[PDB]
Image 1 (cartoon, helix red, strand yellow):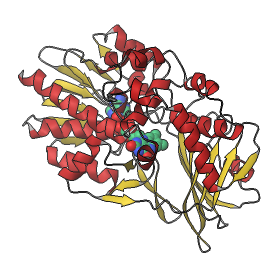
Image 2: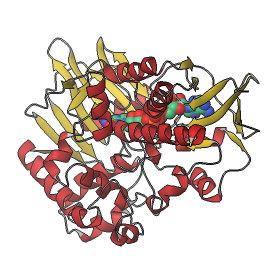
Image 3: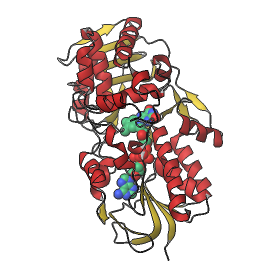
Image 4: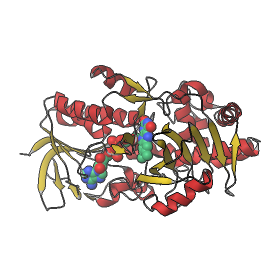
Length: 433
Ligand SMILES: Cc1cc2nc3c(=O)[nH]c(=O)nc-3n(C[C@H](O)[C@H](O)[C@H](O)COP(=O)(O)OP(=O)(O)OC[C@H]3O[C@@H](n4cnc5c(N)ncnc54)[C@H](O)[C@@H]3O)c2cc1C
């Protein structure tokens, strides 16, 4: 007596995957997306006459779940040739910028990274079972900064790795859970070069939006946008779903794939488990934002790290020419450090790194301000990883997915896909046993 067998909440990779699994089993399926677009924390846009990625975009064949889907839908990779860099810069907490030879810059980040992840084999022999070893559980008492303090790195090496880890945290490294970081490294074959190959090297042919829609089309599911879910209530036979318009939708089961930081917007009746409530109140620690700057000058192929007390923590050349100038792709760990949508504030901070540049224009997506992300990529705080089951657990007729709920590449498109396959299996169990 329901409108649908399955309602999937959220049109990111986790929801699109869950919808495709449910739809192909014959279940009448609906996907409700709060924004007026699909993709979630993946979003391809346009800036200065060129395509840009405001959110997630980069994949790799070491990421098993997204790669299998690419082969199901016959999508290849689109390589970002990483080239020989013209410039590598480090900006320290005090704001001083230093130019390093790219080969010595690369050597020192590898030393720091390999020292940071020296024990990945022992802690995560099975990276897709994060709590398999007691050492992983014990490490969940430490932050990343706890480890960095013991590694005896140089001032350069520490700034490099701390900027890198603050990026992965979307936060200062004293708050960043350490096992989450090692686990990702382990997922990449416990190997520096293999893991690095996954970071910003390959994109999906046809974009992330193509794969999401390839799955949703395959699913046959009904898709509705601009429909934020305000409450989910467990009532006889199914669940009852409240949009904003005081529209009411019935389903046998609901798959929630919303970002953890947005559970704040949704009333649950009855109340969810106390372990899950503790997670919703904690949230995830990323406060990242994405920004593109078009400068008049041709700066060539640049790369920069900026330490956590500075705003432009990750700078890369997206494209360059004497005609164009330079389009810089910038990721900001913490949106406290700058207002990416205030252009003069952006202009001063870019000039601190490349003095005397002229900014023609800027484009920014403040993920932490967006009510339907309120944060960026998944980043676990201290002690959160060892309780991941509490967030994964089904709650009666409510199932939970999303990249935060995956076991493997939790900071990635792939963890989102992984959670979608899990949710689809759980739907089948609930609806069919
Ligand atoms: C700046 C940034 C850069 C990134 N770069 C990479 C990369 O290079 N490589 C990689 O692998 N990963 C990257 N990621 C991470 C990747 O994008 C995410 O892990 C993945 O997209 C999350 O998928 P998801 O389905 O779990 O959540 P989401 O994509 O966030 O989808 C959840 C959906 O739920 C919607 N929603 C929220 N609340 C409601 C509500 N009340 N009602 C209805 N709908 C709601 C949201 O609008 C959203 O569409 C990046 C993330 C960010 C923020």
